[PDB]
Image (cartoon, rainbow over all chains, first blue to last red; front, side, top):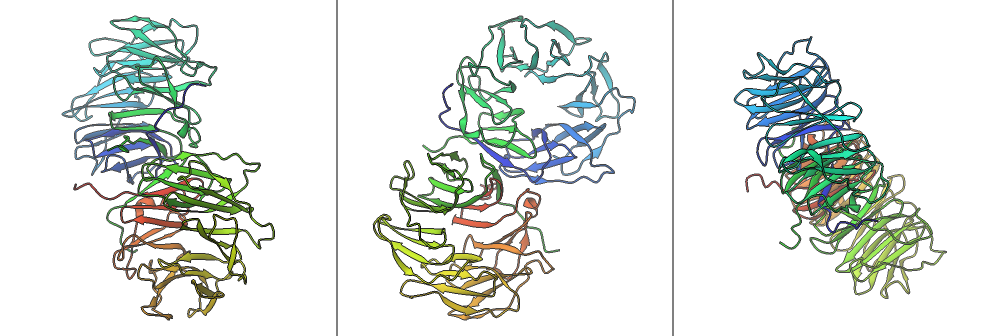
Length: 308
Length: 308
């Protein structure tokens, strides 16, 4: 097979819930928040080593809290059925922000821009901005692209959305008046796309192959690569710890690391029998990162200090 | 209710298995081993933050590895159906030690005494010693007491065994020729017993009460205490982190801490919805400890370094 990874940095944590975790965001290195299914909200004060559940008083518990975002002590959460929560004190207290009921779709993503501003993107790809803590919104992109298979953001605030069926992708950044479609080059269907730290695009396509866009001409693509060299189910997400160190997650404990920017890969065998799919990789710094699993499991990154 | 604990030190880890973990033992602060159901064996090199599964080549996988014990780099494991494994190199390689098939019962506990010696206690309470890496055994206590509800060891090598039905308990230490029975003082049935760091006995009895034997006359007992002040299912284990700091575990995330040697208690609310029973508390030092759960969950102790 491909070589086994030398050191496994990932510790699987079972949170005090059976609900799937959908997002996480940090105020600073120590203080952060995670959100998920069935109105799940938890806090950390030690960088994510331990978590404290927090309950909100609501007439429903059925919310999928899909997105949480902080900029400093200002934080936002959105979910479906439509709900928006806001804090200005690091989540010590949370207020509901009413949403227009004719809002097409449901909130999918919120991004804290600071100073009372946030961008919200719906499940159908409409993009809205508030500058006044959600009291008034204006459409940045009013034409919906329909259900997105995946949605990711670049370091500079561009987004990439994979089409429902993975037949194409679209991009958007401030200044543009609608999503910009792009043809896929591969004969295979797209599963996920996002950005590298240098602002190139990456893609995961069906059947376990990946590729990277060409530096400074993102309409052309590099050659497909098979990280497992072999016929695999497929991968779910790709994320960078450092410019050279890339992780690739998928179902059933499948987790690979590359040390050369995604050219070659090694398998982290130690996590293979963790009883979870690994869906979404969130690095906050080179020594702080998480992988969201199912049913309250996540993985937490542990720097190797055995030779310290 | 009783007060909520101030800081929760326990992080729940999901190991790379669904098998229940039954014991753990450390070579030193960094290097240790855990064992459990369905021939589960895992190693750590970072004090238990991460674990590496290890597979043995065997004609069966049905073993409940019930006990692992190291003294330095010498280690032993025992399980049921009868099996004994031995290592002299810190578990880099493990050898099977054949057991006499007429051995009554199945091995329950092994204790590494160093220099090739170990004490083994069966499920029916017979006690055997080897001085020659298990090539020859001699009975220390040949008369079986039958199925023990629980079995624990003192800092000086005494054992206490609760009777099958919890109607009485017995003790044994070197020099004695059989288990020594004792009457219980309580009208309630015994669930678990063990030793305090000062060598007194403690007991957990049915209905959520505990008590401690009288210093330097262990045949008399102090007053029953209700840690929850309230009618509870019951507790499963009690263990000391320090002479004054005691933990009490039970079913369904129930976990209490005392800071005054077990007189008064606070509940660790943050772990209540971890989806596991907490069965067995193992402290290795004041900053290193674990609680064994079900289906590959354990809790790991995290010292509070937020003010560091």
